[PDB]
Length: 266
Ligand SMILES: [Zn+2]
Ligand SMILES: [Zn+2]
Ligand SMILES: [Zn+2]
Image 1 (cartoon, rainbow, N blue to C red):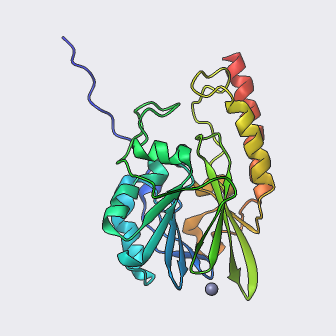
Image 2 (image 1 turned 120 degrees about the horizontal axis):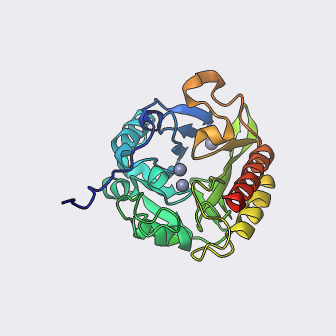
């Protein structure tokens, strides 16, 4: 006689959980997550912004890195998200409890975050995390300002309904640097065609390829750094091989077209 299976934890490649010291991207922007998951700290005179936190177990590491940057828990003002999957929004509930931070997200991302990633359109309950509430709902193109840095939301639905690119202008060498943190454009294991839970999935992805292509984008970063050819473990040449937003979108579209053809054949 055979029991039901044990719950299966969401396990990931070791590099996704490998701590790294803060890596500066521009004057006010740092990568503070792990070697293979992005978490961006943007430091302003009036407090800090975090874009993504990575996995649930990364919360204390993020706070240690924030401390090393001179940002105390009370100084963290705002959390923004690429998308509300466990490997990017994982520690958000805990960060809210341990810091001053409030969350701003679009309605789709807010709804998914509030169910801790459960009943995912594609993953079901396979990949979940502690639920958190959004404090502010943003609309497409809406801006949020913290200590004079202005962040713009660009909706790029597909990977999740609420997938979002965030853009802001930092400086490097007295010159402006237009940073584009573009969300994932993957569809890992997704049913793309005739998906009853996401009927216009293909059209949304196609629109999202165009959105990403057109972002203001001197430097592209992505939640999975490898998608944009970043190597956080490579120090001074971490960003050297980084893709443009144009090249990222193109590569994603080509991958997506191949996946569509494979699905039709499958
Ligand atoms: Zn400044
Ligand atoms: Zn995801
Ligand atoms: Zn991911």
